[PDB]
Amino acid sequence: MISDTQIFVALILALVSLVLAIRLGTALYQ
Amino acid sequence: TLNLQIPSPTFEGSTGGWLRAAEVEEKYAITWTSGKEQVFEMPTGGAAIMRKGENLLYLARKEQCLALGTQLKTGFKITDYKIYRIFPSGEVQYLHPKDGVFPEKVNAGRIGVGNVSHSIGKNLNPSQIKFTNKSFN
Amino acid sequence: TAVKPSAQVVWPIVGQEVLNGDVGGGFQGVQITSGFFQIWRASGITSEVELYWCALAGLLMSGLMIFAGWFHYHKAAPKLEWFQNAESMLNHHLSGLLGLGCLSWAG
Amino acid sequence: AGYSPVPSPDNTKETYWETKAPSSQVLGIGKDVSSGNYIVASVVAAVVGAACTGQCIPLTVSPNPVFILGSFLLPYSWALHVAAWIQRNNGK
Amino acid sequence: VAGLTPCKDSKDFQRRLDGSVKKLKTRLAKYEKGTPPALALEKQIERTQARFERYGKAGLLCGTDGLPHLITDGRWSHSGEFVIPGLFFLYIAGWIGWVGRSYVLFARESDKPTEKEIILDVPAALSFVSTGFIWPVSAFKEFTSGNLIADESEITVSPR
Amino acid sequence: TKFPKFSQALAQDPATRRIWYGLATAHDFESHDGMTEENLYQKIFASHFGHLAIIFLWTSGNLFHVAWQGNFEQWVLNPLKVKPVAHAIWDPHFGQPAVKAFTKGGVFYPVNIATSGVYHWWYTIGMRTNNDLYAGSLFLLFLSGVFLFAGWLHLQPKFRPGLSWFKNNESRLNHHLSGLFGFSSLAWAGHLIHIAIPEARGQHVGWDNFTKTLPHPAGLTPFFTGNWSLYADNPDTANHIFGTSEGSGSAILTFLGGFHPQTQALWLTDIAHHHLAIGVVFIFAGHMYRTNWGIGHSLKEILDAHRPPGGRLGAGHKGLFETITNSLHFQLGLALASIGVITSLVAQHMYALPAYAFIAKDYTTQAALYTHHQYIAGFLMVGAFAHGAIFFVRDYDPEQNKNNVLARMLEHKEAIISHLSWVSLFLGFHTLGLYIHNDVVVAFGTPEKQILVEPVFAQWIQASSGKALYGFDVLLSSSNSVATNASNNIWLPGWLDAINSGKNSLFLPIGPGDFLVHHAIALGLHTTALILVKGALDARGSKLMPDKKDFGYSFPCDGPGRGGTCDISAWDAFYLSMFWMLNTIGWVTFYWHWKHVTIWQGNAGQFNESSTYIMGWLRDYLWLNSSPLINGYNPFGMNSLAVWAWMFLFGHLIWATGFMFLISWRGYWQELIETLAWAHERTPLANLVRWKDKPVALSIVQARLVGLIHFTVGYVFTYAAFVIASTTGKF
Amino acid sequence: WLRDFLWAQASQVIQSYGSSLSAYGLIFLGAHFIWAFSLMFLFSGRGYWQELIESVVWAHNKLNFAPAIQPRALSITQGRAVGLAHYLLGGIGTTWAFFLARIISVG
Amino acid sequence: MDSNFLKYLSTAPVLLTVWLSFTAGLVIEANRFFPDMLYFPM
Ligand code: CLA
Ligand code: CLA
Ligand code: CLA
Ligand code: CLA
Ligand code: CLA
Ligand SMILES: CC1=CCCC(C)(C)[C@H]1/C=C/C(C)=C/C=C/C(C)=C/C=C/C=C(C)/C=C/C=C(C)/C=C/C1=C(C)CCCC1(C)C
Ligand SMILES: CC1=C(C/C=C(\C)CCC[C@H](C)CCC[C@H](C)CCCC(C)C)C(=O)c2ccccc2C1=O
Ligand code: SF4
């Protein structure tokens, strides 16, 4: 019932969150 | 100074001797004069025969050197043992009888290091020395 | 092959008499697992009288041993030269103790 | 000792007291109210709150809002009588 | 009656008694009459029956499981279950503690208190043991005279 | 090296201790090099943002997997018969038998059956389709991104908060009570009224429909007219099929009390009213403290003012304002203790009063949730006490706390610790003695000689709440009581129906076994508290080490000098309290699981009779219920419980491994590793390779921690496997 | 091993109550108790117990009495020895009861 | 009797063993003559 397009949108949001997580990790590491 | 030509106490060899860290970082040495050929215990393990005269021995740790020195002082009556530390550069240093007299007896010239001017009960609290450069003394 | 060996009986105080199980042979007690019954059967004991005599011999030997300990500490204590006889102590143990023990047991 | 100063709200006074009674700054907006005023307020609040509670003890499916509001005067009366004491022993 | 039924009229209690007696009788059936095993099992049966009868008459309450339950709330109808036994304990325990403390002080004021504590002075110990029978009034007398509680400034304490 | 960038003392270590300690001290910011208070607070703020993002991502992953590999849509049809699947299994190690054994849930691929209850939770909320779950997961991903961006932003130079802002207590308290708690619960009530209840009555309401769909036929006129009772008229009938319009009502707010008949859970209207009421209460509570305007209180003023004139508390609460505001460890301890109590309450109340539809009949889910939350509660309580001890070591200022309540606690710590030890010994001696007495008499065949004490106090409390099973006739069991007459026409009918039916876990009947296990729990709580309180109070010093605060919180020891000083630290007190906390929660969860298992199979008499002696627990609970678990796989085949059997043995293994670190200490291993290093250096073809960090044995504190971690993992995994597998194999 | 040996063969010892092996069942439980009790000594250290004894000695001193022989926690070596002794006693006693109950039931 | 032997009997372990054996005998005889007393009879 969950389509591949839906899963791809979820993956894109996950990638955005990963980029933001890397940014936060760097800022905290400083 | 240390003379590297002093013979050694005719040890038979062991696996407790110094390792690559001795050649890379630090290697301690102990020299002592013996009136006769006795049998002593190596701090690394096993028995060795000290020579009549001057004996030089190499170890990996100052604690091993000082344990051997204590054995000589107590078991035997040898108290002329000197301890040195050798770096790969070859910069021998003199350590144990630093001022020519053992630390257990006071000697003129020494400066007190690490002495505090109160009892332990007068130490400050970590809350008082927090976010500051003060010392708990 | 039918009655379970038993040589211990408990007193009926707080219901512990349940431990006196029906081992067999008109007897109820605590089943034993030390093999003493088989030891005695091999030895040829066939009566409680012989076991009483065995107990008497054991008690007499215990008394002899305690007396010997006291005597050899307080009355006649052997010296270090006596103790340091490895050759004699092994000869006597091997021949006398072990050899004569197994010879007497063979008899 | 290196802790940052602790921020407190504006007009924060010292209310610590070892006297017989607090300093009447503990009562805030009611610091200037009279002890007799507090006594009468406490008695009236207790009576009204008890009455409005009794009017609602067998709570129905449609309780009266005014009775609900007035029932909150019984707890209020306690504070008022405590204040009366404080203000009586602070000189008023 | 509190939340349970009296044990004297409980089918569960009667069933438990019957089961115990039947187990004992089954064990007895395999032993000749008059032999020590038969006598022992008959005595066990008698003891079981006496125990159940006494429990029934004691007024104990029994639950659905058929076992007596104890009402340790303070009810005077069930004092014998916890309170009176508890009073007997407290009496004995206070006796022990009072005499032990007395002997500790006695040894404290001796030439070698440690010797008196490892090798006891049993005459004085028996003296204190005897004294222990009025420990409640004696302990309260000590408390009121101030010989029991030590001052805060006379007890060693670690630094804060 | 530059691994522990926050500690040169570790960066300069030539051994593996550098790596280990850099791992274990990464989050102790206060101890880091050149740490200022502002940097500390700002880093904590950003770390909180990251933690919230992690939580959102975790819940989003749950929702996404249930939407993608789940059977939610076919579970909402027959929730009492369909097993909820958590996620699909793709393990290249499975054999065909394993794939077939795990292919369940009506799906056609191996799956895991959820034990978290998320299915019931979401169904109750109003989720019906997989698209709803997918949208929720998308929103939670977006929220995680937003919070990560917020954390990054608030570390920027012009956005980094100040300490005057971090220490602003009044504004934070007002906002957390009013908005975070109050308005948040008000919004939950709004959700329950606009979506959950219509969805439970078969009317779909979503973003495309909620602006045109009235939650109530009267609209908001009853609200804005003062006729609020119109929102309670016409509740759902007793024959309401949850999720359908058959038997539904029109009420949106009520106080029926008790449980919905079909779902066996609390009324959704009751939940909505609960949340609305607590929301307005919290909004009121959030207006107490002073802010940029003149109204309100000041916590400093209140604390300083509160000193009883009798002087029995000394200076009262003077200085506590500064102490708490300047000590993050004091705040951490308070928060951890409160959250621990609340999660225990969550566990205790959520099994007695289920709130989700059909959750009560998911036996494995209920046991899993209860065990989960009790273990979390115990962890949180241990942490609260550990951080109280850390506060005493680090942040305590005696001159500031001159003769206030805290200083008085330290003053009579000896009395506190001695009385706690006495009560612990009291409880232990007598509880264990009664258990052994019962064991011996039952063993000798005289169970009638057992000491069985009826928990008449707890039974009296139950009867007061309205349980007629025991004859007490106190407050609500009494039909002529004022308590009964006051609530007879609001909630008492439904509440009595719920309490006096044996179909639920609400106020389960109790007996002497419950009495004994309760006193065992009391012993456990008191002994864990003893260890933790002693650690906290002796953290600053003792007669043995009267200068412990100089050495800190988690030093190894003080040597064999004064007769031996092993485990002389507050950290070591925590380390032992963690064994005791694992023991107490084990007892609690054993009691819960056995009682509920016996009730579920209907043989409550088994518990009532065997709970009175320890052989009963060992035989009729562990030995009896371990059969399906240990048969998960056997020489004759395997089933889905094979994973739980494997995890059972895994827990046993890691537990026994932790025993290694806890019994064997450092010197032996350091003298063994020396020989190992010698061997490597003198082995040809392997001396070509050389360690860059000198291989050393584990430190004393490190070994204690590692053994504790292994012990805890074994504990938790073993009991998780046992509980879930036994429940799933019995029902 | 866990199922077909321990779980399977522990039935005889755990169902021994009311029989003549009820002693074996009780000893099974007691040996478990002692084995667990050993872990208190094995996992712990002397400093904690010396401080607890300090608090208890304060309690005793508050009543104007305390032993002339000052109470001390066990030495480190003695604590290890006590832990090991209780560990061995508990484990061997558990195996003792298990073996004897099982074999006497099935033989 | 020898005073040294009496002191040896007065030593702590001997006294503890004798006293606890006496107490065990007391309890055992109490349970032998008045068995199964789960309650104080009232
Ligand atoms: C939200 C609450 C909270 C917060 C903010 C903190 C914050 C802090 N705690 Mg902690 N603490 C908490 C809860 C909290 N704690 C709780 C609940 C407990 C009780 C268990 C503790 C107990 C505790 C102690 C005893 C100590 C701290 C310390 C600290 C400080 C240093 C942290 C550190 O060293 O990280 C550690 C870094 C890690 C990476 C942790 C590694 C170990 C964890 C537990 C993982 C083990 C599980 C394993 C990986 C799972 C395997 C799975 C299996 C399937 C294979 C720091 C201020 C230390 C300190 O500085 O004291 C002065 C300290 O000594 N805390
Ligand atoms: C056959 C049953 C039985 C058995 C085997 C035991 C065994 C024990 N009890 Mg006892 N106890 C029993 C029944 C039993 N109890 C009952 C029925 C009650 C209810 C009244 C109690 C109430 C009780 C208490 C209140 C205490 C014990 C304690 C103990 C233990 C130590 C006793 C001691 O050292 O005495 C030797 C005596 C001393 C060392 C002197 C000091 C201690 C005693 C008990 C003081 C007595 C007087 C005092 C004024 C009482 C104030 C009590 C109040 C604070 C509640 C010991 C394992 C003690 C314990 O566990 O401590 C950790 C303890 O404090 N028991
Ligand atoms: C209305 C305004 C507001 C709001 C909504 C928040 C919200 C928050 N602030 Mg706060 N904050 C505010 C104003 C506000 N703040 C102000 C004005 C200041 C400055 C004075 C601060 C200063 C500040 C700091 C310094 C920090 C926060 C933090 C936080 C977060 C706390 C952790 C959390 O999410 O707990 C969630 C808690 C709840 C949802 C409610 C309480 C939970 C209890 C247990 C009830 C449980 C409910 C229910 C039964 C659960 C079941 C649900 C389901 C599974 C069935 C949170 C997002 C911390 C953080 O994480 O920052 C990122 C933090 O470090 N705030
Ligand atoms: C089953 C194992 C076990 C047992 C029995 C105990 C017992 C105890 N622990 Mg615990 N403990 C354990 C495991 C155990 N622990 C483990 C694994 C750890 C982790 C290292 C700890 C860590 C720990 C700490 C850190 C502390 C305790 C404390 C206590 C006491 C709690 C109060 C109590 O129950 O008193 C009742 C007493 C008992 C249950 C034991 C009595 C045993 C028998 C029944 C008494 C009779 C003896 C008998 C006559 C001897 C005959 C034999 C002889 C002939 C040789 C008590 C001494 C606390 C304490 O000391 O509080 C005062 C404390 O601070 N424990
Ligand atoms: C179950 C508990 C347990 C375990 C696992 C071990 C393990 C060990 N002990 Mg023992 N030990 C224990 C309890 C245990 N002990 C206890 C309670 C004590 C205290 C008395 C001791 C005290 C002790 C001492 C004093 C000594 C040992 C020794 C040893 C070693 C034996 C030889 C070896 O290395 O085998 C290796 C085999 C294993 C560790 C078994 C598990 C490994 C499995 C089969 C493989 C898993 C690997 C896996 C693929 C990893 C993947 C990681 C990731 C991808 C997930 C080993 C590390 C001796 C030693 O070190 O000799 C060299 C030694 O001197 N132990
Ligand atoms: C309301 C209601 C309903 C039904 C009837 C009933 C009578 C129950 C009635 C009343 C209920 C009441 C009064 C309930 C009481 C519950 C209470 C008081 C719970 C409190 C629990 C306390 C806990 C965990 C405390 C933990 C403390 C900790 C970590 C302390 C750590 C600390 C240490 C060690 C050093 C200093 C710093 C710090 C952080 C403080
Ligand atoms: C519990 C515990 C204590 C406290 C225990 C003490 C002080 C033991 C004292 C017990 C009493 C004095 C023994 C007498 C009572 C016993 C019930 C009888 C059995 C003992 C005899 C057979 C010797 C330590 O001192 C300790 C020290 C080092 C490592 C671990 C531990 C440790 O685990
Ligand atoms: S044993 Fe290890 S911990 Fe205990 S004192 Fe000796 S060194 Fe410190």
Image (cartoon, helix red, strand yellow):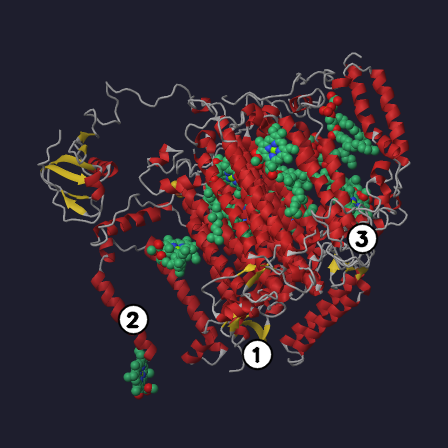
Which secondary structure lies at badge 1? strand
User: Could you give the CA–CA distance between mark 3 and mark 1, rounded to whole angstroms?
Assistant: 55 Å
Name the residue rendered at 48%, 54% in the picture.
F655
Q: Earlier in the sequence, mark 2 or mark 1?
A: 1
Q: Does B126 sit left or right of F105 as displayed?
A: left
What chain does badge 3 belong to?
F
Task: Answer above or below: position of F537 versus C65.
Answer: above
The image shows residue G80, relative to residue B68, as above or below, that is below
Secondary element under disc 3, as helix, strand or loop, is loop
Figure quadrant of residue F310: top right
Q: Nearer the viewer, mark 3 or mark 1?
A: 3
Dot label at residue C33 = none
Residue drawn 29% across the image and 44% down it: F692
Going by the numbered disc 1, the residue's amino acid type is: Gly
Pointer 3 residue: F467
The residue that mark 2 highlights is: C98
Find disc 1 in the rendering and name its residue.
Answer: C24
Badge 2: chain ID = C
